Amino acid sequence: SRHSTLDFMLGDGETILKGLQSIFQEQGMAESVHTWQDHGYLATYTNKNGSFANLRIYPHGLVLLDLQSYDQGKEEIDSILNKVEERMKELSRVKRLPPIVRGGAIDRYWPTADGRLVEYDIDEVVYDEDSPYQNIKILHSKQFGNILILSGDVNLAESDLAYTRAIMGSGKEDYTGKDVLILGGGDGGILCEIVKLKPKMVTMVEIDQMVIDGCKKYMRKVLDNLKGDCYQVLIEDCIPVLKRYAKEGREFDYVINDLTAVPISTSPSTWEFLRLILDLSMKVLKQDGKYFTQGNCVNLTEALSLYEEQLGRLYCPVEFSKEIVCVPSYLELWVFYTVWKKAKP
Amino acid sequence: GSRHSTLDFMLETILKGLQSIFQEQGMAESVHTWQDHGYLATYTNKNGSFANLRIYPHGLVLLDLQSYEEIDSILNKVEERMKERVKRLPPIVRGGAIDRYWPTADGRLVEYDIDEVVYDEDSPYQNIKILHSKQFGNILILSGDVNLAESDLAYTRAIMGSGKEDYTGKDVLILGGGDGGILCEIVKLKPKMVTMVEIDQMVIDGCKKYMRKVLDNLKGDCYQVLIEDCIPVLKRYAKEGREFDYVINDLTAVPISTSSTWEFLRLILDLSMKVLKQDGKYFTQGNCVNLTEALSLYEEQLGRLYCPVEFSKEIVCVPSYLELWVFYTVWKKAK
Ligand SMILES: CSC[C@H]1O[C@@H](n2cnc3c(N)ncnc32)[C@H](O)[C@@H]1O
Ligand SMILES: CSC[C@H]1O[C@@H](n2cnc3c(N)ncnc32)[C@H](O)[C@@H]1O
């Protein structure tokens, strides 16, 4: 469960192999050696306590060491690593990344949307449950506070006021006396920030009661009650609700799409589904209102282009703008869209 | 370099179930069995790649592969077969010509979107890297510590006191600041004078060329850059009784010395208060929010200067840092 690495960038393979072996030999470890017709050497060392090491010596001045614990055993590995560093100076760039914990009861590793390995300062699993719709985790970060992670995707931390600010239009909008629809938003951030501004009505449409309840319990920076003088939370799929509102001719001043990156469907195309949501949102948006949503990470330039393609395929002509926002817990810069109807004639 | 891929299952019959995948790729197997601690199977390939399959006796199976598409396919096969509680983190490149991995001040592993080494030289004072990030632009890294990226105007704003200060007609001293960000931002605000004291000509030269979001000239109407150690210069200004409306400490985390880490920081703070107007303010970058002991040891030094001071702090999100950072504002107590 703890995997430690040490990389040396140099450049004699055999001299290093022989020069390092007593470090392991003196720890009581068993050693086997694989040799290639110069693809170098692989040395494998086994310990009685269930830990092992691998020393890989490439033909051109690259030596990689891996130690894996069964994880006293941590100090033994750290000590070996320190010795190997000492010895390599005698035998003479070095990289010693933080060890990775493998199969930890607390999972600290939440790769970014663009596929980068990032480790978070998680000291506690606060909540980890499966609803009928998604896995819901809330993990405590020392710096970011509690972080909501839905199907393995970081959605929001208690530190992420910048997300909620950006998706409400970055302080440019007056919500006083306005009618607002929020799609998703199970954490309650947007809802609660808007209630503070004295709207006429905010309606939030969230499919998963378990996200509502977990965030009520654990994402605490109003909602003891799901209906108030100027808000209501509907626990349902936003699609039939969008349709029902269009059918009653209802129009909002603002529609804020705070759904998961992959909106939840109960039907047994990716882009088509986003377009549908868009189209349905435009149908309940006043001619002079605005629609806001989170876009995607700034580096996913193809996915942002295919998204903006869909903005051209709506029942009405629209215009849009975008802004790049730094959300603390995201560990990647994010794009946020503002969308509005083109003036009619 | 070598690419290291991992696959973890959180859950002998697993051993024999998976062995097949490696025999078919033509890999030679060696098994080690512990009496109580399970199995380690090592597999080698003629192309110089290898795999280790570690099977703990109670639920954990860890797979690692290393090579100079085949490995991807093996991992895909192992996932399918285990289906007959999974983590597959991005593969780590080891010994790569473009190094992507720059752990945080609190010792977390973080990979950056780095696609180019723009600059990597040793100066007489420190190693200087400028690396291209797709989202952060060029990132200045000094002695392996990310100092600033082109996306990091939040840093510069916070170290200038977060838009609360009026720089017009003012005298300013900057310590370090070799990337030129603070100087340039303050020059735009029309100060009386900005003096910047930066030890390392190579940081200035690197950042002029590569950190682009003036300084073609190191002197102007309302500014001068002194290429020297700021400690002798502070000592001279303190001796002269010279004073500034603002002193901005933009030094490296360990300030450079050409000849108790806390005593050195106390010295710099004490010299800086000495050259500071009674109604002026001192700004600096502090540390990572998680490093509560180092923050505490730092704030202990604030109580150890020639005069009483007060201070406040602000937590700031600097895009490229990948951790929250504390910035300090310090000023003298009245009377
Ligand atoms: C936390 S903000 C993201 C929220 O969007 C919600 N969500 C996803 N799909 C839908 C849907 N079709 N209708 C309503 N809410 C949804 C998720 O349950 C999550 O709470
Ligand atoms: C980029 S901001 C950090 C800057 O502080 C500079 N620096 C570090 N120590 C000193 C010192 N003693 N005097 C002046 N500048 C310094 C470094 O060379 C770097 O350019």
Image (tube, coloured by chain):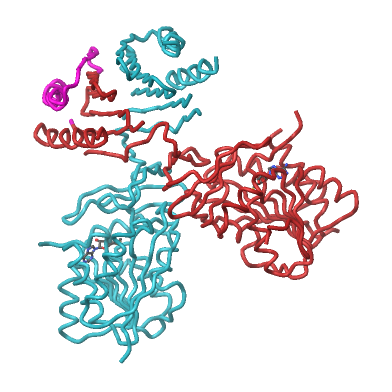
Chain colours: A red, B cyan
Tell me if B25 is positioned left or right of A216 in this view: left
Q: Quadrant of ligand 2?
A: bottom left
Name which quarter of the figure residue A57 lies in.
top left
Find residue B140 and report its horizontal and vertical position in percent.
Answer: 33, 54
Can residue B221 be seen here? The reply is no
Which corner quadrant holds the C terminus of chain A? bottom right
Name which quarter of the figure residue A305 lies in.
top right
Tell me if B294 is positioned left or right of A233 in this view: left
B283 and A83: which one is in front? A83
Name which quarter of the figure residue B187 lies in.
bottom left
Q: Is residue A28 magenta?
A: yes
Tell me if A288 is positioned left or right of B10 in this view: right
* Residue B291 vertical position relative to residue A5 in the rendered view, above or below: below
Find residue A32 and report its horizontal and vertical position in percent.
Answer: 21, 15
Residue under the image location 32 percent in, 66 percent down = B216
Tell me if B305 is positioned left or right of A249 in this view: left
Can residue A292 be seen here? The reply is yes
Residue stretch rendered in magenta on the structure = A11-39
Residue under the image location 49 percent in, 42 percent down = A112
* Residue A279 vertical position relative to residue B47 in the rendered view, above or below: below
* Residue B178 vertical position relative to residue B100 in the rendered view, above or below: below
Find residue B55 and report its horizontal and vertical position in percent.
Answer: 38, 19
Q: Residue furthest right?
A: A248
Which corner quadrant holds the N terminus of chain A? top left
Q: Is residue B15 magenta?
A: no
B162 and B122: which one is in front? B162
